Amino acid sequence: VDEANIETHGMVPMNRLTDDPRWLPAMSERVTRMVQRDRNHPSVIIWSLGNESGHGANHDALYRWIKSVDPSRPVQYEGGGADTTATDIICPMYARVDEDQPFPAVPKWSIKKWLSLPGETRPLILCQYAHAMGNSLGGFAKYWQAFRQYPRLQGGFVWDWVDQSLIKYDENGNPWSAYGGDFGDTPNDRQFCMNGLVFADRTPH
Amino acid sequence: VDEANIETHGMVPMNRLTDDPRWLPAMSERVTRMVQRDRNHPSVIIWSLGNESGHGANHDALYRWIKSVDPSRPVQYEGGGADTTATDIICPMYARVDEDQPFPAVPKWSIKKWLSLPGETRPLILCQYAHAMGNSLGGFAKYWQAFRQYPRLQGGFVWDWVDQSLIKYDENGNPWSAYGGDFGDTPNDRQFCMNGLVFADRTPH
Ligand code: NA
Ligand code: NA
Ligand code: NA
Ligand code: NA
């Protein structure tokens, strides 16, 4: 999945820049210039309009731009409820197998319920599931049971591969794995950079 | 649900008479004369082409006959896998909530999985579920949790209301409830006539 370098997660709402036409130029260069560079690679099967930036009208514009200039690949985008007009795939992040999380505007339905909502035609492939932060991947079996039972459940992408720990050296030059704040960075989100199936040195969890 | 007087369950295959054009006349008069008599009752919201008679080309013919003559009401029929071209409603009997029963030709999918199958848009209302024979209705709550969670699961009809017990009198003329074989009837299917939520005298189970 080749993803454009667009994330506006910290805007309030997440929509603020991606729905503004004054940001459509900046956003189009990050989508279009990706397609122009990577369009010949067979490994790329799906284009992504970015991550966690709500759902703005610029998303719908650039979705249709990709469709027009490269019909050979589906386009996906999770923002604004995972099933917007700018996605060919229902690509939720952390939608649970049986339990609904009915957040206002942007609900995370049961992946099994989500398929059968009236008028919903598309496959579902979680762009992110099974958050692997420390001692986790509890209930991972429950996804794959559901994946195998339901044809339109075609799997997902685990979040994620590598702990984003950095090496620091103490006063005597011993290396140790550091996370949020360990460099005087404030504010910070501490451990939440470490979500990997493997440690930073690629040792398996 | 107003249901035509057509069941050919014991034919091998169930399809045998309902696919035969020579039985289209006999079947048409059981469907058409039902509609002519009961088409003014507001209590009647759904027409049924019959019960357990497989899926024949006569079913499709009489389905279209009802659609043409009375658009007011959906038509449903369970025979030949509960999702045939002769039904507006996915009307399985004894489809389970979570577990598939993948019988060749006529599978009973999990009612939740059934809804999500590619191209399937219809509501699902079990024509028969929760077989209440003797000490039964185990797992009844599992259905209703699913009915409430899934919009396109719109419920079902329990099998069934009354024990088909009959009364016999002992040597003193005290009555007792009889079933299959209690009248010298052979062959017979014994207790299988008693499937009700109530006894024959309408005392609840
Ligand atoms: Na599957
Ligand atoms: Na993280
Ligand atoms: Na419902
Ligand atoms: Na029975």
Image (tube, coloured by chain):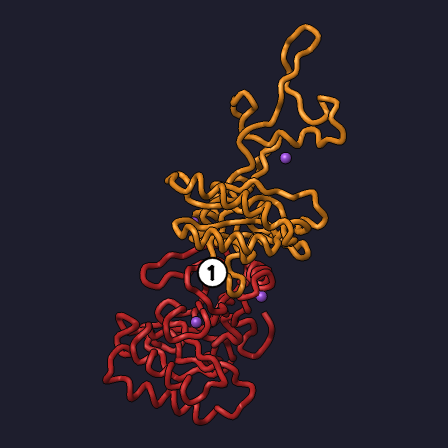
Chain colours: A red, B orange
Other-residue count near label 1 (Cα within 10 Å), few / some / many at <14 / 14–19 / ≥20: some
Chain designation of label 1 = B
Asked if ligand 3 lies within 8 A of label 1, the reply is no
**Element marked by disc 1:** loop
Residue B167: name its quadrant: top right
Kindly identify the residue that appears in the image at 37 percent across and 71 percent down: A84
- A85 or A9, nearer to the observer: A85
Quadrant assignment for ligand 4: top right
Q: Is residue A142 left or right of residue A103?
A: right
Reply above or below: A73 against B142. Answer: below
Counting from the top left corner in percent of width and height, residue A40 is at: 51, 93
- A147 or A195, nearer to the observer: A147
Q: Is residue B66 left or right of residue A31?
A: right
Counting from the top left corner in percent of width and height, residue A44 is at: 52, 85
Q: Name the quarter where the C terminus of chain B is drawn.
A: top right
Q: Which residue is mark 1?
A: B121
Reply above or below: B15 against A186. Answer: above
Reply above or below: A56 against A70. Answer: above
Counting from the top left corner in percent of width and height, residue A60 is at: 34, 78
Residue B114: name its quadrant: bottom right
Kindly identify the residue that appears in the image at 52 percent across and 76 percent down: A162
Q: Is there any visible trace of residue A169 in the rendered image?
A: no
Amino acid type of the residue that numbered disc 1 sits on in the rendered structure: Thr
